[PDB]
Length: 53
Length: 105
Length: 52
Length: 122
Image (cartoon, rainbow over all chains, first blue to last red):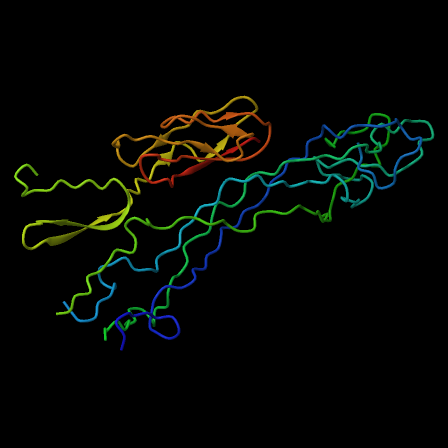
């Protein structure tokens, strides 16, 4: 035996790596109708697939 | 007392219920107004609060004031998110109260 | 659209939506950071090793 | 003590330590564990929503009614978004128009760990 005791390589010790999870959260964003800017007027020529404004 | 000592019944041992907190952070979510496409047909009957779009039609006499070309994107800020993790299990139940060798020479 | 009947014009460019549109969002939270557990001053209390 | 029989202890710091006495002949021992105070304080609000310029005044109530020489070294993560001051009151005056500031208290006379309060700008 030895005067100093330790359990590293092989011994019945305690303590481990905890595992936990976070509760489900949903991100909510508001689509503001302003701040979209504007260029030109009625077509004319308009970019294809552009968002209607 | 005994020849070999340890920290099992009364001592500063390890293992416990993990608890932690996360600092407040801002999460950004962008709600793009495009890519919605078109569904259904010409009314007919249309549900209320429907987003109006353009069909790229050339107005013979009227003016299409509801159709325009986007010039700048829209940036939005999302709300908060999760706070922290929940309780987790520490150690193994079958290995609970495991004996530790501490006998001296 | 507020479901308003067009007085003179024909609002054929506005219609209800029946299929969902896939949207792409940015990154979000990943994991928590390091936190302190227990007190170092009272932690690891010395135990008497005297034999019987 | 005055008669040398008694001994007044004062755990100023933290950590396990032993205190001896009776230097004459045989000296005994007595462990004195300086365990952390862990006086868990609680903020008035945690999920707060600050605005541009306006700063909702908060507070940091400790677990006990009062502490010996109790003080708070108030910190404000992301100080540009908002800042706090004082020990009991916080005063999370905002500067930026958008952001999340993890305003957490810090007991100078006690455990540094304290409850936080995220100040939103939406």
